[PDB]
């Protein structure tokens, strides 16, 4: 049992790459993590053409939960989290795919994002998030 979801994954990995472009430029985030976040968008955008509302909520929540770790790992605060998710909203709304444009406009996806901004606002500030080793591998 398999499906050609790779077509949406290759379109979505660019959405995060352009949205979080400044976070990667700053060394807050990695291109592997930007792809890992967009792999959940691929499922959510394919679900929009299938009309599967339950997928939109679950995939958007899983994406927004993962994204919060990738940002907080860099020492991000609620102000950086709430700017970061907003960039995916533009990148999806401006996307090359009509499935990704429908995803940016989807209430089931957009509601799951609010839970991630309010989660980061409940914590407000980082614990410290500094590193003392090269980690070259």
Image (cartoon, rainbow, N blue to C red):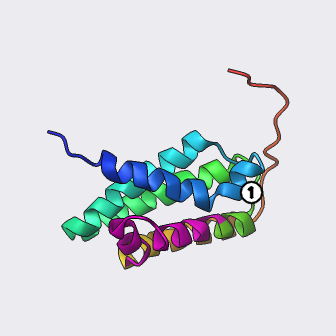
Whether 124 is drawn above or below 42: the answer is below
Is residue 92 visible from the viewing direction of this image?
yes
**Is 55 placed above or below 3 here?**
below
Observer-nearest of 60 and 42 = 42
Q: Quadrant of residue 53?
A: bottom left
**Residue 93 part of the magenta-drawn span:** yes
Residue at 34%, 70% (x, y): give it. Answer: 98
- Locate the C terminus by quadrant: top right
Residue visible at 48% across and 50% down in the picture: 13
**Left or right placement of residue 61 versus residue 84 in this view:** left
Q: Any magenta on residue 21?
A: no
Direction front: furthest residue:
96
So how many labels did they put on this image?
1
Residue under pointer 1: 76
Q: Position of residue 55 (x, y in %)?
A: 29, 62
Q: Residue 101 location in percent, x, y?
A: 40, 72
The residue at the point 75 percent across, 62 percent down is 77
- Indicate the position of residue 105 as horizontal and vertical percent values: 41, 78
Q: Residue furthest right?
A: 132
Q: Identify the magenta region.
A: 84-106
Nearest the viewer among 66 and 19 is 19
């Amino acid at each position: 049992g398999d499906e050609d979801k790779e077509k949406l994954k290759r379109e979505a990995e660019r959405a995060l790459s352009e949205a979080l472009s400044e976070f990667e430029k700053q060394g807050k985030i990695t291109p592997e993590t930007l792809k890992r976040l967009a792999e959940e968008i691929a499922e959510a955008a394919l679900a929009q053409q299938q009309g599967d509302s339950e997928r939109l909520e679950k995939a958007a929540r899983r994406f927004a939960e993962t994204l919060l770790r990738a940002l907080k790992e860099s020492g991000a605060s609620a102000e950086e989290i709430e700017e970061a998710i907003e960039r995916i909203r533009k990148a999806l709304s401006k996307a090359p795919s009509p499935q990704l444009q429908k995803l940016a406009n989807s209430p089931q996806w957009q509601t799951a994002l609010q839970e991630a901004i309010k989660k980061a606002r409940q914590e407000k500030k980082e614990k410290g998030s500094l590193e003392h080793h090269h980690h070259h591998h």
